[PDB]
Structure formats: C-alpha cells, structure tokens
Length: 259
DNA sequence: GCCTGGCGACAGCCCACATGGCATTCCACTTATCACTGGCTTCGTCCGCG
Image (cartoon, rainbow, N blue to C red; front, side):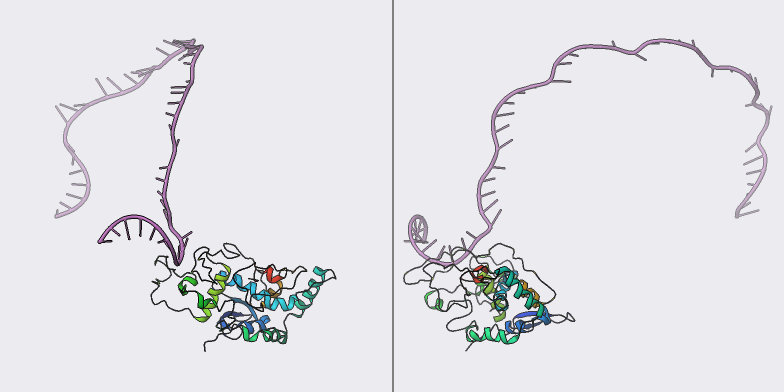
C-alpha cells in the first residue's frame, strides 16, 4: 500500500550551520530533532513555506508554547518559559516523539482514513477529479492556456513527486482559487462554488535567526488565554461540510489552521 | 638626370573731422466636445443549427 510520512520521508530541504554546501532533504521529525544543527529549512514555493512556517509553529512551538498562560501575568510567564527554552538552545527529542507518538499513525498523507490535511470521504462523492494540474501551482488548469511552465495539455499529465505533491497541497490549503471548483454532492448538496483561501494575496512575515530552533521559538504568536485549541490534523473526527466553522481562541485558530 | 637659379626699366611721402538728436498711447476672446473591449475559474443550461 502507498504510504508517505511527513515525519520520516524526505521532502524538507535543509541547510546546515557549517560548510553551506549540499543541502539534504529530510523529514519533518528529523528537522524537528536536529534544529540547532541546521540554519534553516527551505521550500521552493513561498505559499508552501507560508503555510509551512504556520504548521511548524504549531508543532515544535506548541510543545514549547504550552497552550496555557493562566494567571501569573500570562504574557509575562509565557515570556519566562520562552526565555527558559530559548536559553536551553534546543528541544529534547523525547518530547517530540511524544507529540508524534500521540498521532504517529495519523500523519502519512495517503491514509485510507484520516489523510494529512485532507478529507478521505471526498473520493467517493465527486465524479470528476480536479487533476494534479488543477491542484499544482505554475501548472495549467482546464481552461488555462498552454503557454507557460512547460505545456500541460491535460492529457497524460506527468505526476508530481510525492514530496512535490506535499508542497502544493499545503499551498492550495493556504492560497486557493475561489469560485467554480468541481462540485461534490453531500446528501443532495452540489455547489461548484468555492470561497478563497484565508491568506490569499498577502505577505506573511516570519522572523528568522541564526539557527532553526531560534526561529521556531520566535515564530509563535503569543496565544491569549482562551479555549484550548487543536489543529485540523488534531481534530478527533471530521467536521462535515454543513454547519458552522467553530471559533477557536487557541493559537490553532490564530494560525488559521482550525479548518 | 636632377636641381637650382633666373626671367630691361616699373617711384617716393604726407594726409584721414568735429556734434547733435534716437517717440508716444492703446488693445489681447468665446464654446462645445473628451469611446469602447479583453486578456478569472468549471460547469450547466439553453438555444440554435443540422
């Protein structure tokens, strides 16, 4: 069976502190563990990186951010723990595996159920596949002309590398076109219309440092005190199309990652 | 052959201005006008044509 894991499979290009020659691609778990070692991890698509730094800020960061500044001058104490871990200069791998451990079997995007940032049921109710060309950026869609980025005629399209596929999926989850995508029925409801992505047409500002760990630490908005939150992949069960997108005072609702 | 010199006689000098004047009014516009088109998505439905 096909399987890919963000934690173990290599997709994230990584640059080391030394030499600055031959960046190697690594998984998400490895980057997390070897963070002080690497200066940065890079994605060729700025949309892909714009959502990427958002999700990476919810993993390493969440564990370090703690999701809980109650009493004690909240802002002051989070900045105190912040100074404490910033002083350590690194994250203990055992707390990473523990986080990964909670949902270790839930990451491999190609999951039959619970695929990464995806809806698995979707396959059954949509008659026409959008196609890779409609998903991937710089790639021509059905109505798009054949002039740029290699010519894709939408007949025998060359498949995206799985690592490549991951970058695109993440971008479309951030930036995404609005109106007239392919309709899927849900108990009688068919509406090809689609609204735009949450950050669409914007510049995301991520502070950097000398090493990875620094940036990841300095990348988390301070979560105000509020309801405990979780991510789309931290959701216990699927949302369903109908109904209200519930609010989320937690930072996962402030990383625009609740839904 | 090349280079240089020569081919009646053909003028000279002095002289060169002062003074005065040089314009002024006036007049200087209005009206109307000032483009369109497109370079998004997929799909579905309708209308026209065969």
